[PDB]
C-alpha cells in the first residue's frame, strides 16, 4: 500500500534489521514476568490494597470469570503470520477469542502450547509495524516514539487493520501474554480515557512542547502573537487547515484565550490525523476485553501488564548512568542509588518509566538506551530547588534531581514523583 518514497524505504530497512534482531531478542523476551495466578476462590483477588498485584489479580479474575469454555485454535504459517492471524481473528466472533488460546504453527509440532502462544504474540506484535501496512510511524530516529501514521488511509483497509490490532492487544491482556509493539504512555492514556498532558507532549514532540511552554511562559504581544484557533496538518499533501473550534478560521487567539488555546492545542497534537484509526483500535480492543476492566490501572501499570516486567540489573544501570553537574561521588547521587537499592523491582520499573517513558529495556541493557535524537544514556542532572519535586525529560532519559539537603528529603520527593499519576 505505501508509496515507494525515501522515508518508506529507510523505514522498510530499519524494520528488516528488527527481523534480523528478532530471533535473539525473543530469548530475552522469554524472561518477562508478572505474578503467579491468584490461588483463592476461583482466583478471587482478595481485599483491596491499592497495589499493582491486587489490580493484576483483580483483572485476571474478570478474564477467568467471563471466559467462554472449551478452546479456540488459531492456525498460521511462520512466514505469513500477519495475514493468517488477521484472517482467522477477524472471522471469529470476539467472545470466542476469550476461550483458551491454542496457536498451531503450521508444520511445527512440539508441545508447550504456552511457549508457542508466547512466541506468536511476540512475533505478531512486531509484524504489525511493517511499513508496508502504513499503520505506524516513529517521531524520533531509530524506533523512537511509536505513533499512528496520519497518512495510514494510504492502506484502504487501514481501519479494519486497526480493529484487528485492538482485538490482538486485548487477547494479549485477556490470556496473560506479553507483546512488544512499543506503544507510548499517552497511547495507554487514551486506552484509559485519561486526557494526555502538556508534560506528555515533551515525550512525543519536544519541539512542539518547547513552544507551547514559550507561549505560556511569554506574556503575548511582547515578541508578537498573530495566532487563530486553527492548526494546519499535511496528510499526504493536502495542507488541510483544522479548526480548533467550530468556525475556528475567524476565532482569533488573544492573551485572554491562551490557557484555552494550550488545552485545545495539547489535545489537537495527540488526536490530529489519527481519530478514526484510534477509534477502530479501541472498538476492536473493547469487543474482546471491555476497556472498563482497565479502570484501576494507570498508563504505566497498563504498559507493564502488556509488556511484562523484567529484572533491573542495578549494576548495568549504575554503570551506564551519566551525570550533569553531579559526579558519581556527589551526596545527592549516593542517596539516589541507595533509594534505588532499597526499591523492589516494581518500583525500579516505575522509576525507569518515570525517566525514560517506558518499562522496556533494549537487549544490551542500559548502554543501548535511545532518546529522541538517537543514543542517550540514563542521565541525572543537578536541577531544581529543594521545594521542587524531581522532574524528567523522557526525550533525553534525563532526571532533574534538585540538590536536596538530606537522604529523607530526596527519598520522599523521588518516591512521590514516580508514584504520581496525571
Ligand atoms: Na509454521
Image: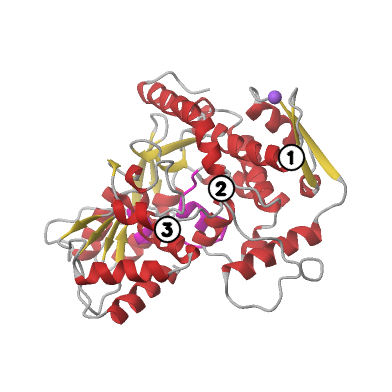
- Numbered circle sitting on residue 353: 3
Q: Residue at x 33, y 70 (%)?
A: 338
Q: Which of these two is toward me, 175 or 286?
A: 175
Q: What residue did someone put label 1 on?
A: 112
Residue 374 pos. (x, y %): 30, 40
259 w.r.t. 111: above or below: below
Q: Badge 1: few (under 14), some or many (20 or more) residues near its Cα, within 10 Å?
A: few
Q: What residue did someone put label 2 on?
A: 31
Q: Residue at x 35, y 61 (%)?
A: 199
Q: Residue furthest top?
A: 4
Residue 229 visible (yes or no):
no
Q: The residue tagged with tag 2: helix, strand or loop?
A: loop
Compared across the picture, whether 160 is left or right of 334 comes to right
Q: Which of these two is toward me, 166 or 237?
A: 166
Distance, label 2 to label 3, CA atoms, is: 19 Å
Residue 140 pos. (x, y %): 34, 40
Q: Residue at x 54, y 31 (%)?
A: 23
Distance, label 3 to label 1, CA atoms, is: 32 Å
Residue 205 pos. (x, y %): 33, 48
Q: Residue at x 42, y 43 (%)?
A: 362
321 w.r.t. 390: above or below: above
Q: The residue tagged with tag 1: helix, strand or loop?
A: loop
Residue 357 pos. (x, y %): 40, 54
Compared across the picture, whether 134 is left or right of 85 comes to left
Q: Earlier in the sequence, mark 2 or mark 3?
A: 2
Residue 349 visible (yes or no):
yes
Cβ of mark 2 under 8 Å from ligand 1: the answer is no
Q: Which residues are magenta?
A: 182-202
Q: The residue tagged with tag 3: helix, strand or loop?
A: helix
Q: Quadrant of ligand 1?
A: top right
How are the colours assigned in the image? secondary structure
Amino acid at each position: 500500500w505505501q508509496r515507494p518514497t525515501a522515508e518508506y524505504v529507510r523505514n522498510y530497512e530499519q524494520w528488516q534489521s528488527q527481523r534480523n534482531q528478532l530471533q535473539g531478542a525473543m530469548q530475552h523476551f522469554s524472561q518477562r514476568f508478572l505474578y503467579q495466578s491468584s490461588s483463592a476462590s476461583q482466583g478471587s483477588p482478595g481485599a483491596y490494597d491499592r497495589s499493582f498485584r491486587w489490580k493484576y489479580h483483580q483483572f485476571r479474575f474478570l478474564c477467568h470469570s467471563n471466559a467462554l469454555p472449551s478452546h479456540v485454535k488459531i492456525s498460521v504459517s511462520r512466514q505469513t503470520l500477519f495475514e493468517d492471524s488477521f484472517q482467522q481473528i477477524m472471522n471469529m466472533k470476539p467472545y470466542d477469542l476469550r476461550r483458551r488460546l491454542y496457536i498451531i504453527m503450521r508444520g511445527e509440532e512440539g508441545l508447550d502450547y504456552g511457549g508457542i502462544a508466547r512466541e506468536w504474540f511476540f512475533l505478531l506484535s512486531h509484524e504489525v509495524l511493517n511499513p508496508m501496512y502504513c499503520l505506524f510511524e516513529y517521531a524520533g530516529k531509530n524506533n523512537y516514539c511509536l505513533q499512528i501514521n496520519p497518512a495510514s488511509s494510504i492502506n484502504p483497509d487501514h481501519l479494519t487493520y486497526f480493529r484487528f490490532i485492538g482485538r490482538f492487544i486485548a487477547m494479549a491482556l485477556y490470556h496473560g501474554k506479553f507483546i512488544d509493539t512499543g506503544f507510548t504512555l499517552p497511547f495507554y492514556k487514551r486506552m484509559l480515557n485519561k486526557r494526555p498532558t502538556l508534560k506528555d507532549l515533551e515525550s512525543i514532540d519536544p519541539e512542539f512542547y518547547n513552544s507551547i511552554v514559550w507561549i505560556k511562559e511569554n506574556n503575548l504581544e511582547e515578541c508578537g502573537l498573530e495566532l487563530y484557533f486553527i492548526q494546519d496538518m499535511e496528510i499526504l499533501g493536502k495542507v488541510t487547515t483544522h479548526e480548533l473550534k467550530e468556525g475556528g478560521e475567524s476565532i482569533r487567539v488573544t492573551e485572554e484565550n491562551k490557557e484555552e488555546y494550550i488545552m485545545l492545542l495539547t489535545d489537537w497534537r495527540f488526536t490530529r490525523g489519527v481519530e478514526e484509526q484510534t477509534k477502530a483500535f479501541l472498538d476492536g480492543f473493547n469487543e474482546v476485553a471491555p476497556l472498563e476492566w482497565l479502570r484501576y490501572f494507570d498508563e504505566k501499570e497498563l504498559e507493564l501488564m502488556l509488556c511484562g516486567m523484567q529484572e533491573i540489573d542495578m549494576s548495568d544501570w549504575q554503570k551506564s548512568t551519566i551525570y550533569r553537574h553531579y559526579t558519581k561521588n556527589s551526596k545527592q547521587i549516593q542517596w539516589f542509588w541507595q533509594v534505588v537499592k532499597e526499591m523492589d523491582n516494581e518500583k525500579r520499573i516505575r522509576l525507569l518509566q518515570f525517566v525514560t517513558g517506558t518499562c522496556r529495556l533494549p537487549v544490551g541493557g542500559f548502554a543501548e538506551l535511545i532518546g529522541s535524537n538517537g543514543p542517550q544514556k540514563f542521565c541525572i542532572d543537578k536541577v531544581g530547588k529543594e521545594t521542587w519535586l524531581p522532574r524528567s525529560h523522557t526525550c533525553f532519559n534525563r532526571l532533574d534531581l534538585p540538590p536536596y539537603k538530606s537522604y529523607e528529603q530526596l527519598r520522599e520527593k523521588l518516591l512521590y514523583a514516580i508514584e504520581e499519576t496525571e
